[PDB]
Image (cartoon, rainbow over all chains, first blue to last red; front, side, top):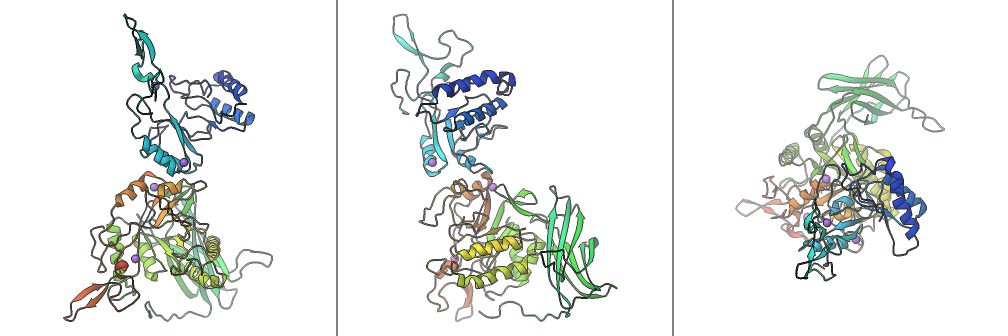
Length: 206
Length: 412
Ligand code: NA
Ligand code: NA
Ligand code: NA
Ligand code: NA
C-alpha cells in the first residue's frame, strides 16, 4: 500500500483531487511499485488509505495498471467501489445490515455484490475491529464468505496493539496508549486494536 | 374436460380486418407518445380501401390517422400491400399502471375512401413501457416491486369455467390485500380476465399452456424437435391473441417443462415478434437462456438448496453469482398450503433491501377444492381422491390464500 493517507482533510479528498498534489502522490505510488514489483508475495497494490476519491487516485490507478498488469489495484476511499479500485474493498461493511451514509454508504456486503452494474469481487480491506474485548459476530462474516463466491474474505483490523511501554517510578514497565506521553490532542486507547498485545501475546479474539 | 369456455359465431365481411397490433413508444420522460397501430386486412385489395385509427380518452378523440393500405418496403421483393401502419402522436399521455390504470380506446375502422364503414374493431390502450434496464424491471421508467399471486381458473361448483362475477371478485380481493400482479398459472386465461386487469390495474404474466412436469426427465418433450411445432402453437397463438392488452407485462413460456432447445427457440421468437415485453421461464433452474428474469420457485431468502443440476440458491446469493445481472422475481414463493405463509416477512424485508429482488408471485390465490354433497344434501369441500380419482395427490390442490368460495384464509 502506498504511503498516502489524508484522512484529516475536510473533505477527505481535498489534496487527492488537487493536481498540485499529484506529483507528490505519484512518487508515493510509483516508487513503491518500482521497489516491490518483483516480490511474489505482493499480489495486490493499494493506492493508500482514507484519502477520499480524487482524480489523482484515478490517474495513479491507471499508471499501475499500465506499468504492472500482473496485480490488481484496490483502494477503499470514496466509497470502496470507485473507478480507482479493481476490488470492492470496504472497511467495516456489515454482513446483513446496511449503513446508508450520504455519499459513501457502507452497504451490507451481500447486498453490495448484487447492486446493478456491480461485478467486482468484494474483499474487505478492514473488518472486525479488534479493539479490546471484540470480534463479536466474526462467525457471521465467515459464514457469508463461504456461502457467497464473490465475497472473497477480508483483512481484520488489526494485528498488534499499538501500545508503548512506559516505566513507573520503581522501574516497572507498563503498557501506555494515547495521551500517556503528554501528547495532546490524542485519541487515547484507539491505537490498541490488535488481535495480539504489543509483546505479541494473543488476545482471546485470536 | 369439455367445452368449458364460450362458444360464439362471428360474422365478418369478406374484406375484413384480420389482425391489428398496437405499440406505444415514448420519449425519456414519457411526455410524448407515439401510438403505432399496424392493421392487416384479408380479402380483395381495392384502391379505395382505407383504414382510420382513432384514439379516444373517455369521450374526447385524442389522435387520428387515415391511410390506404401499403406498408413500407420490407426487403428486395417489397412490402406488405395488405397492411398499413398508422402513427398517432399523443402529447402528455395518461400512462397506464396498476396504481392508475389509465386507458384509451383505439378504434380501427376499415372504410372506403368516400367514407363508407366496412367494419370496425377496437381495443383498450394503456400507454406504458415495460423494460429491463441495468438489471431492473422498469414500468414507465420506475423499478417495479411485484406484489404478485398465482391464480388458477378455478370455481368450486363450475370447476374450470370462469365467469365475470368470480373474476371481478378475485381482482377486488387481490387489490384490497395489496397485490398488484397476477401470474396466469399456467395457461392463457379467459379473454375477459385481461380486460378486467386492464381496467382495474393488475400486472399480468401471460403464460403459455405448456407443462410437461410428469416426463422423465422434465425436458424429454421440450428438448425434442418433434414437439417443437406443438409447443410453438401454444406460444405463438397466445402472443397473437393477447399482445394488445396493457396489463400483460411479461410473457411466460410455460411451467415445469425442464429446459429444452424448443424453449430457447420460442423465447427468441417472442423477443423478435414482441420486444415490448420481457420473457420469463422458470424451468431448468430458473436462470437459463430462455428467461429475461431469474424466476425461481420457492428459493429461500437466506438458505441455499443445492440440488444437483437445478439448485435453488438463496435469492440474495443468486443475484451476485458471477456473470449474473438479471432481476430476480420469484414466479412462485410462500406456498400457502393450509396454515402457512410462515416467514413471509423475511421475503418482503429482502425485497425492500435488495434492488434486483423485485418481488414475486405467491402460490397461490384460491384453494382448488370442489364441492360434494353428503346424503342429507349438505355441501362439503372435497380435494384429491374424493371422487374415486386415483392415483391422486389428496389435499395438495388446496394451496390458496382464500378458500374456493373466496373467503380469506388467515395468511391473506
Ligand atoms: Na467466497
Ligand atoms: Na485505531
Ligand atoms: Na427490490
Ligand atoms: Na399444489
